[PDB]
Length: 133
Image 1 (cartoon, rainbow, N blue to C red):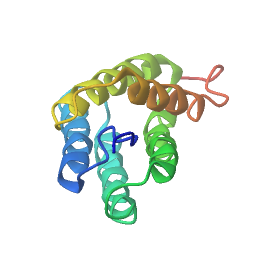
Image 2 (cartoon, helix red, strand yellow; image 1 turned 45 degrees about the vertical axis):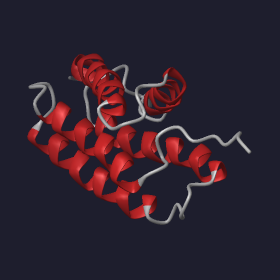
Image 3 (cartoon, helix red, strand yellow; image 1 turned 180 degrees about the horizontal axis):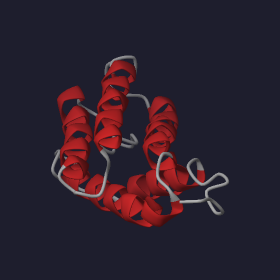
């Protein structure tokens, strides 16, 4: 019996690993602000809270929502960026997220990093085009 969509959300310790690695990576980027690096902290806090609400043996119907949940909360950090710094901030997220994925246990699959990246950008790019900064 095989055929279950188990990417990386298959172990609390594992999933929380990549989440922390993301924060630690971006905190040492030199790109983010003092606010943004702390904003990611409360973001990660939110992740492990809802990750425990995922359930034993994470069902894929939760996983298909969780990637969007993360993305939406990561988008907050990026939405705090001006158009000048946006690209550098996004670059950090897009890179560290991939790194953190494999540094957890489940390697870095393109699909998950794709969903996250796509959604983060889409949920972050709102009217950040014309501005005094």
